[PDB]
Amino acid sequence: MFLQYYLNEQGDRVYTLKKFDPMGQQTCSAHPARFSPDDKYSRHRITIKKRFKVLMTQQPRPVL
Amino acid sequence: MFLQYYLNEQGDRVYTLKKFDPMGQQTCSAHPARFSPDDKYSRHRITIKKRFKVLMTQQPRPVL
Amino acid sequence: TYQELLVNQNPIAQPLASRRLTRKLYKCIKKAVKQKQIRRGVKEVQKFVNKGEKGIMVLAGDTLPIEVYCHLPVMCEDRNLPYVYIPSKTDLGAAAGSKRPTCVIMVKPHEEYQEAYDECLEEVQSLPLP
Amino acid sequence: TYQELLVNQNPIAQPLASRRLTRKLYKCIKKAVKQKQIRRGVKEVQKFVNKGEKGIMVLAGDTLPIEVYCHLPVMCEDRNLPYVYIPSKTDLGAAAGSKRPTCVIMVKPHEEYQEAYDECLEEVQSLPLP
Amino acid sequence: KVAKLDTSQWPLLLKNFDKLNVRTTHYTPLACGSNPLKREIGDYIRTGFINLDKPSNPSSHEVVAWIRRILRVEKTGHSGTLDPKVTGCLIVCIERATRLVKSQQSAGKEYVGIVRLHNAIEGGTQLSRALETLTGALFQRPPLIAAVKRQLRVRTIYESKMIEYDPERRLGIFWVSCEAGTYIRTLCVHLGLLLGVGGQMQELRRVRSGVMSEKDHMVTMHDVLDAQWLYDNHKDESYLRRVVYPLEKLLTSHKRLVMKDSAVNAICYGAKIMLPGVLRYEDGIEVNQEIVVITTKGEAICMAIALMTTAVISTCDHGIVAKIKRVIMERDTYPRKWGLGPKASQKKLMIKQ
Amino acid sequence: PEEDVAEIQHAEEFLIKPESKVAKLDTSQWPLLLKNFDKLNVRTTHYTPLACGSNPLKREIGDYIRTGFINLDKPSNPSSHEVVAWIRRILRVEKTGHSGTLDPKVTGCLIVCIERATRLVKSQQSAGKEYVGIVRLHNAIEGGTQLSRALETLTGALFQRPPLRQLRVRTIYESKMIEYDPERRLGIFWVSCEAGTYIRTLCVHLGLLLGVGGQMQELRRVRSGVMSEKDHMVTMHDVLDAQWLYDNHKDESYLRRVVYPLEKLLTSHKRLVMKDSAVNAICYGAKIMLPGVLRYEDGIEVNQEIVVITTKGEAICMAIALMTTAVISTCDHGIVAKIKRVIMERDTYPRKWGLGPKASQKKLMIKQGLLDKHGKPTDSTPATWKQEYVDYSE
Amino acid sequence: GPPERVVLLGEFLHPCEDDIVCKCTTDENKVPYFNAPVYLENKEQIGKVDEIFGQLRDFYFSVKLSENMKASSFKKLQKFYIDPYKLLPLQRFLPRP
Amino acid sequence: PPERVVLLGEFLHPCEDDIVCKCTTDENKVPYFNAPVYLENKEQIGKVDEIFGQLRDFYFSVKLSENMKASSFKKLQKFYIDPYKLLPLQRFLP
Amino acid sequence: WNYSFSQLPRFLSGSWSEFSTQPENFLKGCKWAPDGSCILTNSADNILRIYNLPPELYHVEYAEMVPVLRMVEGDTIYDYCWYSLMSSAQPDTSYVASSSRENPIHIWDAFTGELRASFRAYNHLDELTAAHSLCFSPDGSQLFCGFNRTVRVFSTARPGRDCEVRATFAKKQGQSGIISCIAFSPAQPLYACGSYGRSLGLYAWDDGSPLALLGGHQGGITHLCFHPDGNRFFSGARKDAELLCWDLRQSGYPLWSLGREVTTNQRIYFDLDPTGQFLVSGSTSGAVSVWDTDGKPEPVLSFLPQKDCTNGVSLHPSLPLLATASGQRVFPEPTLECRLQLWWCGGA
RNA sequence: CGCCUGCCCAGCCCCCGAACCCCGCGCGGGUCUCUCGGGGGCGAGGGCGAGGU
RNA sequence: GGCCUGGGAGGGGUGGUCGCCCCUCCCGGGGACCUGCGGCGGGUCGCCUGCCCAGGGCGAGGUUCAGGCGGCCGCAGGAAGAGGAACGGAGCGAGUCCCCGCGGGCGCGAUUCCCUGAGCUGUGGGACGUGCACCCAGGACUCGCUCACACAUG
């Protein structure tokens, strides 16, 4: 997978083929993680996402 | 009993087993004083709590 | 060492005894315990102040919460009994030959330490009152 | 370079290995690569930890998205395995003897290099919680 | 000086009233009510509650008995039992505030307790993991009572935290946030089984009862006795007015609906809350939602169930905004002012004519 | 001073004073189809609300999921049909659909509609879509200006053919070059296009037009109609975890960040607020007649697709406007719109047609034998009724 | 007496004060009766279900052992079996619709 | 062999084993898939495999017959088709 | 070899260094295993320690003794004991019972030092109560243990909460207080319970029915010993000068009184010979006193192990070895190390 | 091929080399889809003249 | 699937204003309310009907799952003009359920009533006298009494 990105000042994705930003830091991979329906690590993912305050519920609420 | 506490810098109780807090002061017991309904020392408690400016009526009034 | 205990004092712990007066009071308690002439608990001290038994009532100035013993100062002022605070409850218990602390002790007078008792009594009554 | 790699870091990448502990871990991995004791990638490490193996699980702190390997920390805590985050993904793969980056590897013990393994293990066991 | 105060510093249910949606600004004020904080001491106590710090010897029903001797009132309730040796936050509702006990008893509690383990564990992290395991919806057997075997039931533990661990005495402080009716003694037994060493709850203290906590407004039993004494002997209310708080403080989380003075007495007699009497209404009123209906002086009239949403109120011109759940205010606090309105007058006129 | 504020709170009297100024609402922050509810033109305020439905955001969790969708970030192994089948299995739900088939190795925006939101899938499938792909050229090029010129050339209404059928027309609205790498002969392009545009085919045509030849290396969908990759986008892990958290901790919080009500897809459309009595009639397939219109938005035009909503902000149906805004404001009677697609279930709101004045009049005349059994005129009908009553069947 | 058949109740985890803690692994996540006899696959009674605890879909149970049994006897991941009439469905404990 | 032939398009730069051609058919008429492409003398060059570009101005690639080579054709060299394998824009446009 | 206190006991190695880890540590008795293989010691650090019989005895200077096991409790250890029918030839018999504050009665394996079993005593509220005393029956089938106003009887075969409860105080009548010690008659089918409430009680083994209730002592009773005759037995108390001699015949009143200095709230142990002729006891002063039981017991010897309280004394069942445990609670003032010791008491 | 063991084909994951591409003056240096070769892990989709009850 | 059908005008052939066939030009028609669900849009050996020689085979048709990606057919619900400015409430009391770990809690007296126990414990533990106050309040259902039957006065 070649497609990478870095976030703009506006907040949107700037797509790129390079593995570093103009400002030095690493570009994230554009594609989401692989998923399989047999996954039984929901407890595990939630447990540590709570610890570091990165669970989706704990973020600022969206504008509707 | 076993539960003690000391106050942090924003006035929250910080519970602990240890008799001294991290700054070397003694920790208070978490539990209130034992009460008797036949207590006849109401005059006496008001008398010296007024004297040392620690009666509840002399404190800053709560914001509601 | 004394100045470190001064951090732990109550809102109501006055008049606090001087560093040397604290030492005199402990030595008087040791002699009174040997003679079987003290009362230790609030439970006890309160009972015999009600009966009207005289003595110097020594209080621990780091007692919390204050509701446990803060009635006793006024009970003494009703009957003109001399009372005084001291830095710590652990040392007050230690003075009576005990590992556990206590928040109040009342020392009764007796012949064997009458001069030491009167020396303590004299300085207690001389203290400035808040 | 170590201090520069903190800019690239991941929200969940703690406890992070120190500059010196990172150096010790790479050399323990390289020794384990020669003896073929390591297990590389999520699929293998997840399989072997579930199967019943024990050792030290070295995670990469540059990994994104976190969903690829954020289940592994708790898989260790269920079986009391030690784990630690090192700064880079590319360095982990180079130390593991691969020409691609890698997000996680598990180092197993061996009689050949127990001195270096013990220095890492005890230091990693000692790491404070965030 | 009230003119200088921002609306965010107005007391209790009048706080941030300008951010409620305004239906109409016109009504005829009546000299009937007071602000809940300025109620005459008798009425103030009869509509009030105490955020008590329960002592460690008596049962919670003994404590509320003692409070109703002291204050000289006929009714009290108590926001969930604490066991005889347990201390902490016990909301004691007095008289007309006892209408609110179900809302207080059903609220989420928080506890700080000590578990004693019967053998050594590896360390504090192992206890911390067993607490994470017993987060979420748990099975707990309710204890036997009068030889009546209650069935296994489910209770949620929202959060858990391992505060301290002492390997010498094998003692561990824990903090638990949980649903009402959770057995913390049972939690410590399970926490011991999960570790494999065994365990018992050494000690317990409730640090929160829904809206009230030990952080603010909490008083001991001595304050309650002492405040009453000062009122009895010196005719000073000051101490009582810091021990007892008006029941409006328990309702500050609820969505509000402000009513005209004309409507107040009608609602107290059992009339449904109609839309022509609504002055202001909060954002986020939903259908079948429990709301608080208040006067323009901030007094709670009733707990009501909303039959219109916020948006529906904005569009309509008449009709049932809410039905009553429980009337708080007494009848004839305000005068009868119903039947005087334009449509209601027209109805009675056209029946007569 | 904090203490000075506390002292004023207990000393001085507080009162919501009477005023003569006009009561002005602010509905700019209200959720979804209730946003700027104040700005809609008001026909009438006089009706009886029913208290049956809910605000879309605050439906009970079962009803919330059944009337909702997921802006999914599709993972790179499975097919789009397999992905929605997983979501159907996870949420323990009967039916699921999606906003456009992404190929197995393609990622990005896939609006997965759940149960009763699956009535919108045709509208979502026809919506305009944006892609970010990588074209891999078989031979070298002079520079990235040439590949940009090829994308400039293929901006417009194009001929296209499916991958391995008939020739088809597909418009590409806008195209752009993000960057090009001469070493590995890969070029990132972004394209906005209509639904059903084949991007594999576009990459081949870029290759032929340049002369070097080429194919699609990889693809990602960044937009699917109204939803984008920076708008509430969620992964398959989130969907699984949010359901698990609801199952094991009884916590709906995570589900309500994952799933959104179908009304969020319809926020672009012009609104027509119906009276609560008219709602279930329209769900049964009635005409949207003028007596039931409470409010109507500015700038409705003839043959425009409008969303018809309740007073609580629920979507009843998508509909085609027969009257303009100006006509609705001035006319006495008529058909305001006709149904395109009924979203809301039957008997969500109760069955309250035939109770009105003019409807009850017609029922009475049929009972009296003044009209026929099928509501049609006779010779005996009064000239007042016969002239006034404009029967819409005609 | 011995039941006609027995269904998988759970697997052995660590012992705890002379009774055995077991992870529950029932089909359809069914919950055992209190004091329900626990059998090994040979249909020999080892004990009775004492405690039931943990999350709804990942719960444990302790087993008060029989007169002749010892907690040291059991090995890790050893399976235990229950009379299927002495289970209840999970739906019972889940909230009313 | 065709009865008669009509212009198909002119030669554009070659591709890998194909020749790309810009269409210049009368009234923009679109050629059929797999239709034989001819020279001015009715000698078949190849067969039309792919058709692409905008509806008004579009291109077509020709899969060459085995004898021909892509490099041999001159710049703007014209190519032909039988008129029965052409289609109007009005089929595709609406 | 046979016991003889015609001469002062000769010193044999003891342990002092490990007890000095904690400040103000002190021993809380010592007990030989009933086969005579090793000695068990309690201490104020809440650590039971087992020391093997010295190899240098059978093999002169002896090195400082080192314990083969340390088995840690998390709270004050109220009582501890060897299994009644222990033999070092059988791993199934070699184990140590131990009770502790707010904890179950733990059973420790005497070879490996692992927690082997747990007996648990709950009150009517289902809260765990700790046993203040422990005693195995002379068959080794049952584990008797004392609480406030009640003895419980756990079956040794079935470890757990299951127990036969025996109330000693019913409707303000019977033996009151915490039952601080149990002991069984070698010959008769009975057991004797001492309490911190002054009284002694005798009870039938099979039923738990009271046979007698005896006064005598002026403080809380701390220890009991039956003579190998079966008729005669002895008792001692805290803050009480007399060690009272009793007899099952001519009951109701103690036959003799033996003086010893006890000025603390301590369990100052005493022990008989295996033959039953001598009786040894410790003291708060330090002086270990010896009496010949064979009339009133005649004073034979008094010697001083150390300049400190001798809380524990234990006599070896086969060999002439006296063990002595030392130390006591130090009381503070506003602003010698304790030790186990062995002693040869054989004849010349 | 009822069952079990073993072998072959297909599929999935990891490492190395060659060709191709890029840069410099037959040579040197640096990357990556597809294709070809080698090594490691894994049979129940298909086949088997072998072994066991 | 090189769509289907009717009328008028002109030219050619054949037979007894008339019938039939072919070509060219012009014009009309292919209808049947609204909504929801399902099926068709080659290849599923899983079921049924039919055909042939508790079994086997088949170029046809159909139902329920699985797979692939507007038009027609079938079934079901409606045949809808959109009502109602007191509807049908409250507060108490009782019976029955839910809730529901509650002999323990409090005080005083005398031998300082005993006790710094290694036993919790003097900010409290116990013994004996003695007295005292606790064991509800809520919610739901059901059958009474009281107060109203209220659209909220520009």
Image (tube, coloured by chain):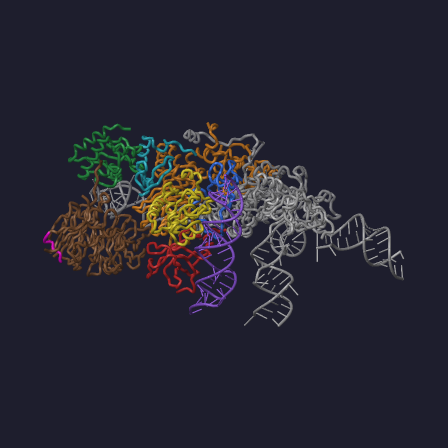
Chain colours: A blue, B cyan, C green, D yellow, E orange, G red, I brown, J purple
Q: Position of residue I244 (x, y in %)?
A: 16, 52
**Residue B35 visible in image:** no
Q: Is residue I73 left or right of residue D37?
A: left
Q: Number of marks in the image?
A: 0
Q: Position of residue D82 (x, y in %)?
A: 37, 47
**Which of J4 and I35 lies nearest the eye of the viewer?**
J4
Quadrant hosting residue E173:
top left
**Which of D46 and E114 lies nearest the eye of the viewer?**
D46
Q: Position of residue E258 (x, y in %)?
A: 51, 36
Q: Position of residue E267 (x, y in %)?
A: 51, 39
Reply above or below: G45 against E99: below
Q: Is residue E169 left or right of residue E1?
A: left
Residue C39 counted in the magenta span: no
Quadrant location, the C terminus of chain E: top right
Reply above or below: C95 against I343: above
Q: Is residue E230 left or right of residue I23?
A: right
Q: Which residues fall within the magenta stretch?
A: I1-7
What secondary structure prevails in the magenta region?
Answer: loop
Q: Is residue E273 left or right of residue E173?
A: right
**Which of I326 and C125 lies nearest the eye of the viewer?**
I326
**Which of I22 and A2 lies nearest the eye of the viewer?**
A2
Reply above or below: C2 against I143: above
**Residue D57 visible in image:** yes
